[PDB]
């Protein structure tokens, strides 16, 4: 099949031909920011493998207007190509008159043009507000995975690595940025200038970046002499201080850790006003949402600091994992994403131990397990075809699970030997691609006995879901049963590395497991045992017999006799098994008693988090009797810890997190004191007019409480357009959405659609925010459902925005009716809409919810009433 105008397409696969091979791109881009469009040309040094009559590469929404091929030897300079477009595959065919010669280089060259992108992809247009209120424009590129083809025609696959030499024409008012340092700038006739950037090292197309803006920067040098710069709106340079501080510390770390220098001479980090992704690891020119990069001490909280540190860590980890060593294809995207996600941990634990990220890491794995316990889940490494399916590859499986199995592997292998694996892997594939298999070979190959580790992880990456390790203890015998953990299978089996402890010795006994079942002995008929120490392994464990009761009991007495991460694990698993049917809800609720003793914030916040969830499920239905006793059990129990909370910014990171956590809970639950203090602080802030200062850690709590009055809601909204801290704006918007008036919420949404006051990039989260609230769950469903067509103009399905707009408004549903409506809406989508994997997940999720209610609801009712007694 073929098009556009009659004829044919010499090639049919959406994968590209391996015959033509790019070695270098001379790229010239001439953008106009008043005209809001660009004009550009390129010259690709090709190498022909087998002889051909046609050249196939990617192009999209690019008006190509002059195709030639030149002869370094064949012919002279030169000859003209016939250009053939085929949109349904985002390809174009270049037709040669004289068949090409194997083993000879050529130069494809063309002139193309288009308008600057209209939303977050390819070479698009963004704006921002200045302190004076001036609206300003920049042109920025975002290409992963398949948008480079919208900027310049090219062999747009991660394998087709090449060097890139980029030139940009610009006005005097702007600067031009790109992957590589600027070699020279040359004055042109009509007063124009032309930046010439140093040729890039070999790199995939999705990492090519360029920006013309009037931004401001702060610069510094790492030990190995790299110039790191933080670019941002001129009026925001003050917020770039931490980023620079962290940037250097991290790049340094990574160089030492990977034993590989950052190749380039400079690394820029730039804060983009309108930025869809969280950030992008463009080699040498990493782009960020302002909330991912900018920090303001007067307005950015403790967790904020931890956020931007984390995301900075993530992106620098990419320069090695992803940039230097790139996956062959988007099926193995996890090799880039899972590792970056993991290095966040390592790199931040190393350079910033005081941020206590180590205790926050289990959340990563927990978050994904929620979805990995559904049938509709998928294996880390899975096939991907159409762009949409490639986009879909970016999720908590590729990221969280990916990072979580490595953390398992590292534990199995010890830091050093694991580290050695990664030094070798990155070195072995520098400036080239790699495949899932390639990795495991290097991680296990750090006499004559061998690491078959490959066998082990290969199953971890190739099969969906998470294992449930059952354990029976008849005296000194332990039955070991493995299952596919499900939320209430046949064929699954993992080589799952076991860990455990006895009540006797806190000494850690390791072990393996490769068969459907085995058994182990116990050198002491002991009280309890605790499998999976610190939850370092990607599996759930359920104790048969008195195992669950003894372990719980232990916590009720000397709770300190169990590792804190062991606690967090017990707490996490106990409730998961309730949803699995392997436990009865009151046993979980009966564990949350020792939380009166618990001082380790991680564990205390984990337990509390579940009780807080139940409240919100109850509160989302009109289940008043339960939701209320639930409220009054949190206010009475935990009254000690709640009352110790200062409305300040003092103590450690976990101190500050605990405070914000607790204080939010109280104000959520309408605790008289709490809501009177926040109302006070707020009224002061307003009646003083910004002059007074709310501690950052309560900034959101305060704004949200002040949001309840219409005077406050209007002030907060008006102060939303005036703020120069996007982190504050973030908190104001959340507060704006804790309102009870449908029109106030509706307005926020409508303003979001418009994307003038509230940037488009925030629509997904905003919609999500509103939906969680009882007063707003219907409104959102209505909206998404009704305006779905206009939503698909703005976003891709499945862009994270759309995927998130969907689940954000439905996943929390828990009634048969809603399941019908949603089931029926996903149906409607059966056209340009259908299909997305998210459809399944959501449905399986809404059903998991209904069943949890039926299987466990009344139990909640009486465990709570049993307490009110
Ligand atoms: C991880 C964080 C530091 C930012 C990260 C940047 P990157 O370094 O992972 C980049 N390479 C991905 C950019 C991208 C995202 C989605 C589709 C195509 C291309 C991210 O993905 N962004 C958003 C949105 C998102 C994409 N996949 C996800 C998987 C799970 C959760 C969120 C996301 C975010 N908030 O992480
Ligand atoms: C983009 O287009 C604008 C006009 O829309 C160009 O600006 C004009 O350029 C000509 C030629 O130098 C001058 O005679 C005018 O005085 C300019 N007007 C203004 C207000 O700038 C601009 O040079 C173009 N930008 C680029 C970099 O191509
Ligand atoms: C394309 O990029 C590669 C790197 O992937 C460049 O190769 C380096 O070139 C320098 C200068 O000649 C050598 O000293 C290094 O040994 C090369 N590095 C490696 C690891 O190969 C190459 O120079 C670039 N090509 C062009 C045309 O500039
Ligand atoms: C090109 O030549 C190689 C070497 O024989 C051959 O294996 C390959 O199939 C050819 N590629 C195509 C299909 O043009
Ligand atoms: C964090 O860093 C410390 C050294 O400061 C190291 O001993 C520890 O193993 C690291 N933690 C983890 C779990 O990676
Ligand atoms: C709990 O156990 C710890 C560790 O031995 C001990 O220090 C403490 O005295 C015990 N507390 C109680 C409540 O018995
Ligand atoms: Zn990433």
Image: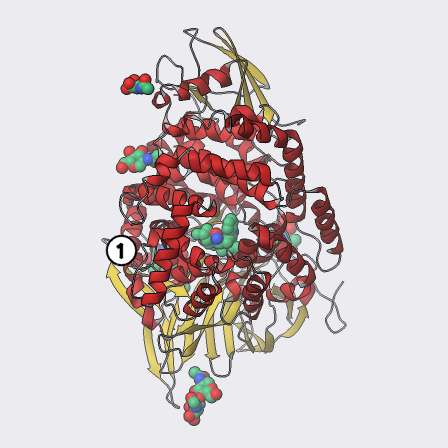
Q: Pinpoint residue 461: horizontal percent, then vertical percent.
A: 54, 36
The residue lying at 70 percent from left, 50 percent from top is 822
The residue lying at 67 percent from left, 71 percent from top is 84
Q: Pinpoint residue 7: horizontal percent, then vertical percent.
A: 75, 71
Q: Pinpoint residue 191: horizontal percent, then vertical percent.
A: 37, 88
Vertical comparison of 713 with 395: above or below: below
Label 1 environment density (alpha carbons within 10 Å; few <14, some 14–19, many ≥20): few
Marks counted in the figure total 1
Does label 1 point to a residue whose CB lies under 8 Å from ligand 1? no
Vertical comparison of 781 with 819: above or below: below
Q: Residue 56 versus residue 299: which sits nearer the camera?
A: 299
Vertical comparison of 457 with 22: above or below: above
- Coloring applied to the structure: secondary structure
The residue lying at 52 percent from left, 44 percent from top is 398
Q: Residue 731 versus residue 464: which sits nearer the camera?
A: 731
- Confirm whether residue 439 shows in the render: no
Residue projecting furthest to the bottom: 190
Q: Secondary structure at mark 1?
A: helix
Q: Quadrant of the N terminus?
A: bottom right
Write down the quadrant of residue 584 in the picture. Answer: top right
- Confirm whether residue 825 shows in the render: yes
Q: Pinpoint residue 204: horizontal percent, then vertical percent.
A: 48, 57
Is 773 left or right of 823, judged from the image as shown? left
Badge 1 is on which residue?
Answer: 245
């Amino acid at each position: 099949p073929v098009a556009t105008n009659g004829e044919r397409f010499p090639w049919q696969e959406l994968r590209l031909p391996s015959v033509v091979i790019p070695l270098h791109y001379d790229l010239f881009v001439h953008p106009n920011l008043t005209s809001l469009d660009f004009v550009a040309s390129e010259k690709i040094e090709v190498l022909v493998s087998n002889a051909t009559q046609f050249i196939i590469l990617h192009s999209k929404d690019l008006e190509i207007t002059n195709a030639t091929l030149q002869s370094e030897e064949y012919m002279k300079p030169g000859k003209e190509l016939k250009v053939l477009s085929y949109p349904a595959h985002e390809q174009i065919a270049l037709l040669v008159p004289e068949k090409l010669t194997p083993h000879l280089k050529y130069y494809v060259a063309m002139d193309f043009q288009a308008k600057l992108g209209d939303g977050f992809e390819g070479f698009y247009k963004s704006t921002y507000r200045t302190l004076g209120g001036e609206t300003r424009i920049l042109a920025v590129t975002d290409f992963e995975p398949t948008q480079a083809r919208m900027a310049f025609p090219c062999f747009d696959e991660p394998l087709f690595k090449a060097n890139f030499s980029i030139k940009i024409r610009r006005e005097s008012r702007h600067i031009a940025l790109s992957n590589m340092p600027k070699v020279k700038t040359i004055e042109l006739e009509g007063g124009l200038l032309e930046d010439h950037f140093e040729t890039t090292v070999k790199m995939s197309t999705y990492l090519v970046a360029y920006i013309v803006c009037d931004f401001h920067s702060l610069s510094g040098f790492t030990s190995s002499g790299v110039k790191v710069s933080i670019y941002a709106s001129p009026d925001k340079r003050n917020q770039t201080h931490y980023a620079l501080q962290a940037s250097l510390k991290l790049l340094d770390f990574y160089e030492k850790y990977f034993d590989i220098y950052y190749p380039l001479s400079k690394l820029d980090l730039i804060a983009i006003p309108d930025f869809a992704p969280g950030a992008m690891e463009n080699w040498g020119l990493i782009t960020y949402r302002e909330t991912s990069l900018l920090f303001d001490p007067k307005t950015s909280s403790a967790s904020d600091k931890l956020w931007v540190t984390r995301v900075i860590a993530h992106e620098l980890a990419h320069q090695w994992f992803g940039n230097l060593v790139t996956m062959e294809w988007w099926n193995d995207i996890w090799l880039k994403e899972g590792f970056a996600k993991y290095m966040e941990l390592i790199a931040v634990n190393a350079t910033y131990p005081e941020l206590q990220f180590d205790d926050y890491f289990l959340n990563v794995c927990f978050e994904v397990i929620t979805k990995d316990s559904l049938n509709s889940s998928r294996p880390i490494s899975k096939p991907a075809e159409t762009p949409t399916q490639i986009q879909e590859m970016f999720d908590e499986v590729s990221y969280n699970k990916g990072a979580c199995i490595l953390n398992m592997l590292k534990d199995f292998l010890g830091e050093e030997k694991f580290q050695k694996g990664i030094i070798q892997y990155l070195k072995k594939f520098s400036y080239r691609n790699a495949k899932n298999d390639d990795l495991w070979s290097s991680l296990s190959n750090s006499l004559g006995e061998n690491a078959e580790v490959k066998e082990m992880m290969t199953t971890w990456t190739l099969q969906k879901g998470i294992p449930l390790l059952v354990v029976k203890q008849d005296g000194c015998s332990l039955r070991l049963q493995q299952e596919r953990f499900l939320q209430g299978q046949e064929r699954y089996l993992w080589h799952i590395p076991l860990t455990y402890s006895t009540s006797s010795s806190n000494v850690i006994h390791r072990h393996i497991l490769k068969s459907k079942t085995d058994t182990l002995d116990l050198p002491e008929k002991t009280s309890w045992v605790k499998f999976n120490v610190d939850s370092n392994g990607y599996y759930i464990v359920h104790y048969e017999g008195h195992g669950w009761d003894q372990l719980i009991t232990q916590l009720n007495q000397n709770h300190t006799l169990l590792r804190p991460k062991d606690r967090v694990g017990l707490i996490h698993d106990v409730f998961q098994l309730v949803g699995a049917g392997r436990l009865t809800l009151d046993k979980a609720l009966d564990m949350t008693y020792y939380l009166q003793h618990e001082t380790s914030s991680p564990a205390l916040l984990e337990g509390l988090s579940y009780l807080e969830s139940f409240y919100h499920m109850m509160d989302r239905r009109n289940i008043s009797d339960i939701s209320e006793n639930l409220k009054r059990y949190l206010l009475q129990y935990f009254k000690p810890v709640i009352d110790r909370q200062s409305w300040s910014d003092k103590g450690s990171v976990w101190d500050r997190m605990l405070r914000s956590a607790l204080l939010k809970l109280a104000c959520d639950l309408n605790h008289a004191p709490c809501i009177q203090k926040a109302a006070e602080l707020f009224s002061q802030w307003m009646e003083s007019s910004g002059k007074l200062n709310i501690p950052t850690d309560v900034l959101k709590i305060v704004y949200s409480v002040g949001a309840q009055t219409t005077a406050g809601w209007n002030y907060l909204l008006e102060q939303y357009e005036l703020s120069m801290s996007s982190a504050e704006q973030n908190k104001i918007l959340y507060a704006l959405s804790t309102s009870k008036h449908q029109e106030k919420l509706l307005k926020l949404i409508e303003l979001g659609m418009e994307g003038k006051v509230i940037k488009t990039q925030n629509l997904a989260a905003l919609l999500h925010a509103i939906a969680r609230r009882p007063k707003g769950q219907q409104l959102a469903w209505d909206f998404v459902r009704e305006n779905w067509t206009h939503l698909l103009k703005k976003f891709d399905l499945g862009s994270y925005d759309i995927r998130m707009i969907i689940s954000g408004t439905t996943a929390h549903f828990s009634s048969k009716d809603k399941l019908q409506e949603v089931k029926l809406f996903f149906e409607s989508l059966e056209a340009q809409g259908s299909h997305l994997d998210i459809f399944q997940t959501v449905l399986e999720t809404i059903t998991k919810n209904i069943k949890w209610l039926e299987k466990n609801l009344p139990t909640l009712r009486t465990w709570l009433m049993v307490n009110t007694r």
